[PDB]
Image: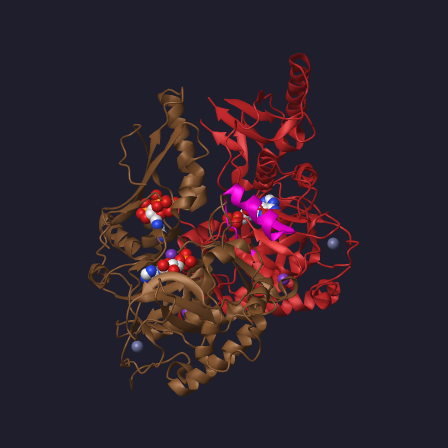
Chain colours: A brown, B red
Amino acid sequence: GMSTQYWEEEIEIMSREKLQELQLQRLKKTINIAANSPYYKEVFSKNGITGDSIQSLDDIRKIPFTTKSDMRANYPFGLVAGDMKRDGVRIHSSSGTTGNPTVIVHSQHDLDSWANLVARCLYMVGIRKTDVFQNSSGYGMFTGGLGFQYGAERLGCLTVPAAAGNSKRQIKFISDFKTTALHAIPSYAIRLAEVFQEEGIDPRETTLKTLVIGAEPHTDEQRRKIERMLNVKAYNSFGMTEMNGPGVAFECQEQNGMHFWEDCYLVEIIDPETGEPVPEGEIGELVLTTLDREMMPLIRYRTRDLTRILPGKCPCGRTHLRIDRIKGRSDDMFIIKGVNIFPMQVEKILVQFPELGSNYLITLETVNNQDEMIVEVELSDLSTDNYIELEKIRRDIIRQLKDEILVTPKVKLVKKGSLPQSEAVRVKDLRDN
Amino acid sequence: TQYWEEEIEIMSREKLQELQLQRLKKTINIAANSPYYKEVFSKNGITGDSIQSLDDIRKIPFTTKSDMRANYPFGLVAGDMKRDGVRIHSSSTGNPTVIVHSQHDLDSWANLVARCLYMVGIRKTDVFQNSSGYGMFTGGLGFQYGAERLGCLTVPAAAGNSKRQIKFISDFKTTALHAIPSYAIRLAEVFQEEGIDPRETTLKTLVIGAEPHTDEQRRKIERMLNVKAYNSFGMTEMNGPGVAFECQEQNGMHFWEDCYLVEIIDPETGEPVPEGEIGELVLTTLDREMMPLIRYRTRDLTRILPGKCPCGRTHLRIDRIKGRSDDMFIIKGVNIFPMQVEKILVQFPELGSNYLITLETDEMIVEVELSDLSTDNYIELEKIRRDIIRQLKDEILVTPKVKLVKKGSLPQSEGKAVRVKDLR
Ligand SMILES: Nc1ncnc2c1ncn2[C@@H]1O[C@H](COP(=O)(O)O)[C@@H](O)[C@H]1O
Ligand SMILES: Nc1ncnc2c1ncn2[C@@H]1O[C@H](COP(=O)(O)O)[C@@H](O)[C@H]1O
Ligand SMILES: [K+]
Ligand SMILES: [K+]
Ligand SMILES: [K+]
Ligand SMILES: [Zn+2]
Ligand SMILES: [Zn+2]
């Protein structure tokens, strides 16, 4: 409380009364901006949403939800509200070519707001400009790459844009550049600790002090295991491309719930069936509204993420609400190696091969603390192909899947009728979650 | 002609010389704080009074890749890295060299990339796609920050996944693309495979670099995609992209002399070459503060093109990179550069764009893919193959073995194309 340091004290410890008037002011502004987009112009016209519709924060429930299906239907720029040709500076797109992906368009204001939120998060968990920050997240279209890169530079850290994989090079950068802060997915942080002891280095005797872990569900125990293996303090990091990427919700040094930055987001916990707000503190679907986005704001977006608001004041002194861990989702999406994948993306690739049967199964397992994706697909007795030709097709399946879902899966061609029958195709998740 | 920074881009030679001298003295005073240049200046008697003219830089010895490897990782860091260091980049076997940047250094680098892009006609209204690898590769974050500084709608596609690259161009209406010359050809091929005419896209401008390539190789890219392609020079040591770049005249790459001091030195004597002769490119940073580099031997061979450019810019122009010193190969005691082979192969329209030089025990094998548009028979193609052997023999002064291979048979590299395979 008294010894707690803040990036933006006036906002981070702002009274609930002053937070409510800030959210209402930014909510009205967001709706007036969003009304310029072809999608929300249509939505507001059909539901009688005008400039007088929002007088309180509860009036947001007059506006219907924004679903992923709606966003896919308006791909690529149906929800763009600003002047993209003049002020649009970046596009963040989701994976795929078999279906319409998700596109978020940002202006310079939007990138600066996002970079400030990431800097706020990093400063909160004790990271300073004197720290050496290494980002093991994939770059390019992945928001974790450029997101933490801009945020850590804004804070003033000596950044190490290592990007994904090559654990020996990751260990080399930590040892030679004296890395103190590291961003990694929980399973990769365990892999790095393992690679340290393979190279004859004690994973507890490095320059590492702080770890930022996210992109996928993990228990408090899995985080405590990471903390013991590397002799560090690990903090839960929440984000999604739709909400910028990282910097949305983050743990404080109390490591009890993730503080949601309510100055930039309006949080709603809704019953996934009725679509009504859940009783205070119960598990429901996370529904979010951007409050500082201008190029492409999102109003009441159904994230399909399940969580709850943790009650009571936090001893760090911050007034921004805390959410519990995200354990699962209300949709059919699965996360492997921190990458979001829909089972339809896999099916749309497999159906193109006439040598394959219709029956397929996706299995998610943990092998040596690392997550693996196994795609079993039955053979069609219609093919006249021998071993050499079928193996070439199996390698072509791996390659086309890798390009679509942005992860390399294990593909096994199984006997016709070997896989069990159910009748939508299920994803068998055998991981400890 | 439109300029990003007119006052600097058309600045008189007299005013450029006093700007370079002012920034050279500042660079040497900053570099003196690094453990490496503190020792170098102490042993060679380099003080604050040693530099009074631009010619006085020759009092300071050269900085080689070996000196940088010997002082890896932060032996040449001059600034306060803990307080002002904001990024570490690395260059593409052994111990990769590291460059440390402050916020000033990143902003200077971003401004140079924006200056380059604006010069070739790219504006904030353009949709810029970067197919360069991100992470530690300077091409990724280098063009990303530069294009955002200009105000382009950026598409950080990163390396590979050609089907997704084509999808982004088609759906986001990409007008400007950054790619290595060999990957630009691969994308044009993938467009045709997906039933799209590579000449009927929204693409208008292409930025190509990293790989040594001929003018005809670039003209092939321009015809395949119906675009204007511009040569982009850079290296991690000098920030990455934005160092040297062609103007709309497409005749020599303008070197930004406000941020770099250019020298063309004889690799044997270590003295400046006669005005306009081919020699080793030796560079000094003039706007870098965290880790400046003084008279760095790049290993790149080029020459300064004489005369003022019709675009009105007063900044000197360098010719195409002949190749790096490590690219040179010796067969039967004769020195050969891979660009000598490419400059011959590009003149034959019956040949493709992908080729491979193999050295075995000594024999030199030159594999080159056939064109898809080729309708020639065996007798005519064999006559062309014999014409290729003759023209190669006269140029490289050794008789090589030439094999005409199937289109797509030769392997495509993940990054820069490997043109020489030495199996000796
Ligand atoms: N800290 C976290 N804990 C659990 N799941 C997370 C976390 N951060 C992100 N996710 C999940 O990843 C999704 C965002 O993925 P993406 O759009 O690729 O950044 C979220 O909607 C969550 O389902
Ligand atoms: N436009 C270009 N033409 C030819 N070679 C280039 C070009 N740009 C860069 N290079 C080469 O690539 C090197 C820089 O590589 P890197 O620092 O790994 O990006 C230079 O020193 C040159 O040898
Ligand atoms: K720093
Ligand atoms: K994720
Ligand atoms: K723009
Ligand atoms: Zn707290
Ligand atoms: Zn010019």
> Considering only vertical position in the picture, is A403 above or below B363?
below
Q: Position of residue A83 (x, y in %)?
A: 63, 66
In the image shown, does B361 or A193 lie closer to the viewer? A193
Residue B419 at what x, y percent from top left?
A: 54, 33
Q: Is residue A202 above or below residue A8?
A: above
Residue A422 lies left or right of residue B386; in this view the side is: left
Check the image and name the residue furthest to the top. B379
Q: In the image shown, does B74 or A288 lie closer to the viewer?
A: A288
Q: Is residue A141 left or right of residue B267?
A: left
Q: Is residue B37 visible?
A: no
Exactly how many numbered labels are in the figure?
Answer: 0
The residue drawn where x is 66% and y is 29% is B344
| Residue A195 vertical position relative to residue A26 in the rendered view, above or below | above
| Res B321 → quadrant | top right
Along the line of sight, the residue nearer the viewer: A47 or A183: A47
| Magenta stretch bounds | B155-177
Q: Quadrant of residue B348?
A: top right
**Can you give x and y, in whole percent of width and height, for residue B192 in the image?**
61, 35
Residue at the far right in the pictured view: B310
Residue B400 located within the stretch drawn in magenta: no
Is B175 within the magenta? yes
Looking at the rendered image, the quarter that the N terminus of chain B falls into is bottom right
Q: Nearer the viewer, residue A242 or A7?
A: A242
Give the residue drawn at x 21%, y 59%: A229
Q: Position of residue B128 (x, y in %)?
A: 61, 54
Q: In this picture, is B300 found above or below A359?
A: below
Residue A387 visible, this orientation: yes
- The quadrant of the image that shows the C terminus of chain B is top left
Name the side, left or right, on which A104 lies relative to A192: right
Left or right: A282, with B236 as reference point: left
